[PDB]
Image (cartoon, rainbow, N blue to C red):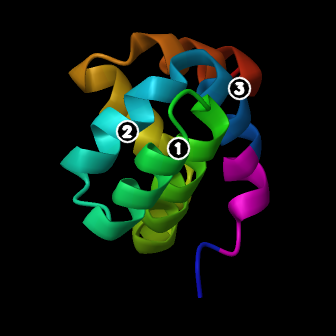
Amino acid sequence: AAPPGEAYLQVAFDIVCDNVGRDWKRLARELKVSEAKMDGIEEKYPRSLSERVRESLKVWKNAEKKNASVAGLVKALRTCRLNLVADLVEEAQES
């Protein structure tokens, strides 16, 4: 059901998570992720970058479908302000 190509996206979600990890919560609110999920992850995890972003990133990744590829998130994150993760996925792809 979710993006079957989660393997490639998961690699990008890994370098970017440990880099701008807190900015996914910022993007999660923009993506209108389940408010209930944020309530549990935020309250349960007061300082875990991995714990808060993973749940919020999981729901966003499922709704992305074709946008589950980096071209989707890298285009959006860098155009707005997340140049940090853009540089990460960028050098990873070499191009």
- Which one is earlier in the sequence, the residue at label 1 or at label 3? 3
* Position of residue 72 measured from the top left corner of the image (x, y, whole percent): 43, 47
**Residue depicted at x 27% and y 63%:** 35
Classify 10 Å Cα crowding around label 1: few (below 14), some (14-19), many (20 and above): many
Identify the disc placed on residue 15: 3
Q: Nearer the viewer, residue 78 or 23?
A: 23
Mark nearer the N terminus (2 vs 3): 3
Vertical arrangement, residue 67 with respect to residue 22, above or below: below
Q: Identify which amino acid the numbered label 2 is placed on.
A: Lys
The magenta-colored residue range is 4-10
Kindly check if marks 2 and 1 are in contact, taking CB atoms under 8 A apart as contact: yes
Q: Is residue 57 above or below residue 62?
A: above
Amino acid tagged 1:
Arg
The location of residue 70, given as percent across then percent down, is 55, 43
Count the marks: 3
Circles 2 and 3: CB distance less than 8 Å?
Answer: no
Q: Determine which residue is flagged by label 2.
A: 25
Check disc 2 and report its element: helix, strand or loop.
helix
> Which quadrant is home to the N terminus?
bottom right
- Between residues 91 and 34, which one lies in front from this camera angle? 34
Nearer to the camera, 20 or 87: 20
Mark 3: which amino acid?
Answer: Ile
Q: What residue is rendered at 59% in x and 30% in y?
A: 49
Task: Single out the residue that lies furthest toward the bottom.
Answer: 1
**Judging from the image, what secondary structure is the residue with disc 3 in?**
helix
Residue 57 in picture, x, y percent from top left: 50, 52
Which residue appears at 70% of the width and 62% of the height? 6
Overall secondary structure of the magenta section:
helix
| Label ID, residue 18 | none
Image quarter (top left, top right, bottom left or bottom right) of the C terminus? top right
Q: Which residue is mark 1?
A: 52
* Mark 2 or mark 1, earlier in chain: 2
